Amino acid sequence: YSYTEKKRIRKDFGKRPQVLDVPYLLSIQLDSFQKFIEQDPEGQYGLEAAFRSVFPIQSYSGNSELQYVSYRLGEPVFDVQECQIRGVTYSAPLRVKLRLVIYEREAPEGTVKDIKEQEVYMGEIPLMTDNGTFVINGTERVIVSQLHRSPGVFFDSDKGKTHSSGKVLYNARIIPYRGSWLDFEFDPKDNLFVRIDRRRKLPATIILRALNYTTEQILDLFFEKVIFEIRDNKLQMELVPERLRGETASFDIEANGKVYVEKGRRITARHIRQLEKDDVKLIEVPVEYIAGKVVAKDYIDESTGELICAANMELSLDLLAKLSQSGHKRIETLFTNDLDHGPYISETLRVDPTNDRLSALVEIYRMMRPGEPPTREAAESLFENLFFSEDRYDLSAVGRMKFNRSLLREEIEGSGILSKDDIIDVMKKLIDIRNGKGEVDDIDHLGNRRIRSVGEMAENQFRVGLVRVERAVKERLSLGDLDTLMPQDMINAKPISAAVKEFFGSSQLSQFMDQNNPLSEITHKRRISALGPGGLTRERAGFEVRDVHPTHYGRVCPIETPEGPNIGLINSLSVYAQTNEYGFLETPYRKVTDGVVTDEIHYLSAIEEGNYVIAQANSNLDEEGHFVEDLVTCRSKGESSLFSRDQVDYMDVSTQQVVSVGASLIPFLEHDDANRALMGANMQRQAVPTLRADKPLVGTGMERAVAVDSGVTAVAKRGGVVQYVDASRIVIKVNEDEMYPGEAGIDIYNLTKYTRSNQNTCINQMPCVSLGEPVERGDVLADGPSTDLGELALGQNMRVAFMPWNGYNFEDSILVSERVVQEDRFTTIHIQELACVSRDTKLGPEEITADIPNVGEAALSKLDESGIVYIGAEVTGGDILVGKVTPKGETQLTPEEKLLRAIFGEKASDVKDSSLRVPNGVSGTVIDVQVFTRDGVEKDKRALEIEEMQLKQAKKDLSEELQILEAGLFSRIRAVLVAGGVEAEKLDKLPRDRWLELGLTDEEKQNQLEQLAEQYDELKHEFEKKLEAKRRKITQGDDLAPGVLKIVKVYLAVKRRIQPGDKMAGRHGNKGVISKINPIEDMPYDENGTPVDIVLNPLGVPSRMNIGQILETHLGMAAKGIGDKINAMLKQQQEVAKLREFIQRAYDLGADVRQKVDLSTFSDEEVMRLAENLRKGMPIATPVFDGAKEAEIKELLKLGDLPTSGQIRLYDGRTGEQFERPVTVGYMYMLKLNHLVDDKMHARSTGSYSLVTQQPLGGKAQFGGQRFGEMEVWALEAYGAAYTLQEMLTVKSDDVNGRTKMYKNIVDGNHQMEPGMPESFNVLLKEIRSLGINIELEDE
Amino acid sequence: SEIGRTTDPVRMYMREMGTVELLTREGEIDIAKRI
C-alpha cells in the first residue's frame, strides 16, 4: 500500500468511495504568493502588474521618462533558519531594471537623445517559506486571507427602518477596488438621490447634468413618450395597449369601433387584449385627461421664438391652448403610471436646483469641497477625477465583471473606470427594483464576498509604495539635472521598503503564527477574516454578517469559528474549497449526466451553484452510478428539498466537503451538537504536544493529510533505501529509477531538534524509519511535534469511566489517575528564551561578568568565567543565568546607613546587580546559549568558545554531507563501471579517487562517468565555498539595536507535568480542569483489576448534547479490545497464521465498508510488524458523516470479547464494592490544552506602580495587581463593606503615603490603615484645571 | 458666498489668499518703487 501506511493500517469504517483526493491544504497561501512573486509575461499578476501600473513615469514636461524593463528577486542574504536565529526578516532583494529615456526639446516625434538603463534596488520582499509562513523580524507569521465585499454594484434597501411607515427604501452602491463610492438611493417621497463618498445627498439628476445630458436627454433616457398627435380637433393620441395596463378609466375608448369600456370601470387584461384584437393605434381623448401630464420636450414658438413650455412641466389646458395658437403637430409626454413606470426621475428633476452642466459641477464641488469657492476648471476636474480617471478610480477586473454581471451585460471585460452608460444603467436598475422588476442583492452571499490573499494584499501595498516613489520621481525629473543622473539616483528604496515592511509586520492580517501543533498551523494558514484593512470592524459588525449563509456550504466551515466577540468574522476554509481566478470561493461537485453520477468534477462558485440542483453525498448510488433511489435530497436555490433522480445536475464530492480541516478531525461529529462541535474544533488547536505522541484509536482519516500537509514531518522527496538513520538526520540512497543523470543520488534530511515554537512549546523531529528500510516517495521519514508515524497525534488515549466520583468531577472537573502522571502521558516540554541585553548607558557600559556585588559564591556556582550559565545546568527560579552589572553613581547615603558603613568600614558598590535570573517558579535546563556581540565590542571567552564550536560544527556538517554525497557518487561510478567494461576486482585495486581517471568505451558509459566526475568536482568546490560562506557569517558582527553592546539569549527547557488546574479536553467540546490526581488503588477498576485512567462526569453529556464522546468511548473500548487480543497473541507467541486470521477478521468487519485490506498479500514479517503496531489498540477511521454506525461498534465490541453495551461492572478502589450500575468505560482521546495553571497562577503583595496614576501595574509579566473594577466596587457597596472598599481604593492601590504606612503597620502587627486621598483623584483635579475649570475641594 | 460653510483653517486661508492676484514683472517693479 505504502511502506509507511502498512506499518499500521487504520481500519476505515467509511462506506462512500472517495472520488476526489483531499487537496494540498496550504494551496491558498502558496498559490497566492506564487502569483505575487513569479515572472508574469503578461501584466496581470503580482510585481509585474504593480510595475506596469505606475511605469512609465513621465514628468510635467516632454524631456525625459522613466520606464520599467524588468525585475528580479535576488538571493536572500540569510536563509530562513539564520533569519530566525538572528531576528531578521527572510526576504529577497528586489532589483528592477529601469531606463531613463531622454527626449530632446523640439521634434514632431520627440525622439531620444539617449537612454541610461540600469538596475535599481527598490526594497526587499519578504519571502514565503515552503509551508506558507513568513519570517518577519525573526518570528514566523501568517498572512490571513480576507473575506471582503467584492467590487461592483450592489442593490440593497432598508426594510421599513426609516420614515416610521414601513416603506422600503432602495439604494444602489458602486464600490470600486480603489476610488470613491457612488450611492444612489430613494427618499420616502420617491426621489432619487446621489451621494458621493457617503457625504450629503444631492438629487440624482445633478450627477446626470454633470454628464452633459439636458433635461430632455434625461427624460428620453428614463422615460417613454406618450404622443398626442392632435389633428384639427378631437385630440388624437397614440397608444400601445400595454400602456393602459391597470389604467384608471378617465374616458371611454371608442376607436375602430365604439366603446369597449365605459366610465367607472378600470382596465383589466381582457380589455387590453380585445383592444389589440381591434388593433387600435389612435384614440380621441378628453381635455381634462391631458391636464396633469408631463411634457417631455422644450416647445417654443416660431412667432416670437422664446419658450412656450419647457421640458418636465405638468401640462394643462392653458399650455396646450398656448401651443395650439402656435400649431404644433405632435406633443410628446412622459408615460408614467403607478406601480409599473414611476415618475421618480421627473419628480427628482423638480427638486434639484440645477439647470445646466456648470451648475451641476458647481453643486458637486460645494458638496465635496465646502467653503472653497468653485472655479469652472476645478469644478470640471473634480468630477472628471472622481470616477473617470484611471489613476484615481479602479473598478477592477473583478469589479468590472461583477458590475457587468449585475447589469445583465454580455461582456465581462471593460475599463476600470465608470462611464455615462454604467451610471445610467445603475440608475435604471435601481428604478427597475423600485418598480418591482428586480430584487435587492444579498450582500452576505458568497458570490458577493471575495477572498483577498497575501499575494494580492502584498501587491496592493507594493503599488502603494510605488506611487509614493512615483511622486518623487516625477518631482525629480522636473529639475534640470537631467543629463548627468542615472536612474538609481532618483529612486528611493526606503518608501517602497516601508510599505511592504508595514504590511508584513504591522497588518491586522499579518498574525503571529499559531504554532501549538500541526493543526494550529494549518488552521491558521487556512483562515479567512472579515476584519482587516478594507474589511469590517468587529464592534460594528452586526448579527447578519456573523451568520451561516446557505452559500457557505462547501466553501466556509459552519462550525470552526471563534466563540468570542468576533464570531462569524473569523472563518475557516472548507476541506475542498478553493478560490476562483476572481477570488470567489468555489467547491467541487460531481457531474450527474444521465442519472449516472460521473467522476467528472466541476468547481462551482456560489452564483453558479444556485442555478443547479445538487444532490447530497449521503445519497446512495449503485455500481453503475445511478441513484438507487428515485427521490433524492438536494439543494436547489439555497433551499433544500426532494427531487426526482432525473432533475439532479451535480452531487457533493464527499461527506466532509462541508467542514473545515479542524472539524474533519472530530469523530462522530454528526452526533455532536454544533455548539460543542465548535468548541471541540477550537480546542483541538490549543493542544500541547506531549513527550511521546499517541495516535488516536478513534480518528477520522484526515490525520495523515493534516500531518503531511503541514511541514512538521520529514517527507521523502524521492524513494530509496534508508542509508543512515540517526536522531538528527536521515540519509536516503535514492533508487536508480528516480535519479537524474550526473547526480550523487543521496537525499539528506536534517531534523529539527528541540527548538521552540511561537507558543514556547517544543518542536522536535524524530525519525520513523529504521536503517536499511525501503522508503517510497511521499513517505514520512521523521515525525514532527504531535505526529505518530505520520498521523496527526494531538493527545493521548485515556481509559475513561463516565461516573460521578465523590464530587471530584463536579461541574466539568476531571479526576486523573496517578498512573497518568507516572507514565508521563501529558508531560510537555516548553522552551523559554531569556535575553540579557548589555547596553551603553550614560554612566558607562553595562558589563556581563561573574563578579556580582551582594551575591555569594553559591549563587555564582553555575556561571562560567564570562558570567554566563553553563549549558546543561539545572536551574530554578532566582538562579542567575547571565551575570550583569550596571554602573551607577551618587548613592546619596542616609546618615544612619552612613554611620552604619562608618562602623563596619564596608565600601559601597559602584555597580548594581542587573543580572538575568530564572523567573520565579520556573525550573528548567539550560539547553542553548547565544551571544550576539556588536562590532567593536570584544568577545568574551564564552562568545569565542561558542563561535569556535559553531565553526567546528559548520565544517563538520559540511564535511559530513560531502562524505555522504561523494560516497553516493562513487557508488554510482562503481555501478556504471561494472555495467560495461567490468573492473569489478580492479576497482578495489585502484585508489578510490582515480576511478575518475578511467577512460571507458563510450556507447553511453563514458558520458555518464564523465558527468559523474564533473559532478564530483563541482560538489568538492561547492563544499569549499559553502564553508567560507558559513565561516564569514559566523565570525561577522551582529547588527544589534543602537545602544546595545551585546545580547545573551539563554534557552530553558522545562518539563511540565500535569497537575490540578491544567485544562484537559476531548475533541467533542468536553473541556475540563483536573481537580485531583488520584492514587491508583483509589481509582475504579474492573473485574480484571485494571483501573480507570480518568473519571469524567456523565452529567456533562446530556445537556451539552455531544453524544459523539460516548460513541468515541464505545468505539475506543472496541479498538483497544482488538489490540488487547493481538497483544495476547504476541505474548503467547502464537503462529503468524493465527495473527493473520484474527487481524483479517478485524479488518473485514463492517457493513459494506469501502476499504479492503488483504493480509494474504502481506509477508509474515510485514504481518508481524503490523501486529506489533496494533497491539496497543487497532486504530480506526470514522469519517465525518460517513462514520461507523452503532451496530458496527457493537459488532467490533463483540469481536474483542467485550460487552456490546459498552458498560462494564466497576469496583470502588477504596472499598472494593461494586458501583451499583454498569459504568461506561472506554478510551477517549484526551488533549492537554495550553491553559496550564503554571502560566495562570499569579499573586502579589506589593510591587511596581504606574507613573501618572500610582496604581499597581497590569499583568503577571509586570508582577501586577488584579483589577478591582467597577462591578466589584458595586459588589462591595451592596454588602456594607465600606472599610474593605476604602482599603481597596486608597491603601491597596493609589494612596501613596498611606500604602507604605499600611505596609509598616502590617509588619508591626497593627492592622490599621491611615487612608488619604487617592493619587488619581489629584491627577483628575490637575487635569480638570488644565482645562479652563476651577475645580476645588471645599476644605471647611 | 462660502462664508460659514467649512471648518478647515487651511481652506479658509486658501480662500482668502486667492482673492489677491499675481503681479507681472512690471507689477513687482512699481510696488518696489512705491516702497
Image (cartoon, coloured by chain):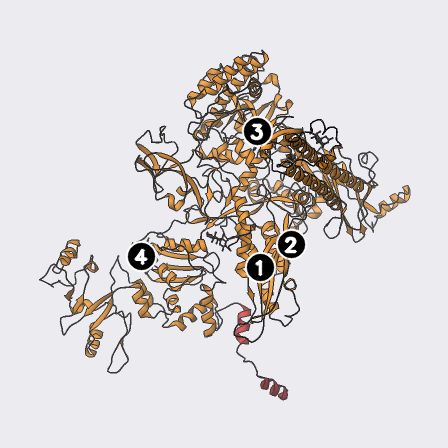
Chain colours: A orange, B red
Quadrant in which residue A774 is drawn = top right
Q: Which residue is mark 4?
A: A432
Host chain of mark 3: A
Q: CA distance from mark 4 to mark 1?
A: 49 Å
Callout 4 crowding tier (Cα within 10 Å): few <14, some 14–19, many ≥20: some
Q: Earlier in the sequence, mark 4 or mark 3?
A: 4
Q: Where is A1337 relative to A551, above or below?
A: below
Query: Which residue occupies 53% across, 59% down?
Result: A52
Going by the image, does A840 lie left or right of A1070? Answer: right
Amino acid carrying label 3: it is Gly
Going by the image, does A91 lie left or right of A617? Answer: right
The residue closer to the viewer here, A1247 or A897, is A1247
Amino acid carrying label 1: it is Val
Q: Where is A212 relative to A641, above or below?
A: below
Query: Which residue occupies 34% across, 42% down?
Result: A612
Amino acid carrying label 2: it is Val
Residue A997 shows in this picture? yes
Quadrant in which residue A627 is drawn = top left
Q: Earlier in the sequence, mark 4 or mark 2?
A: 4
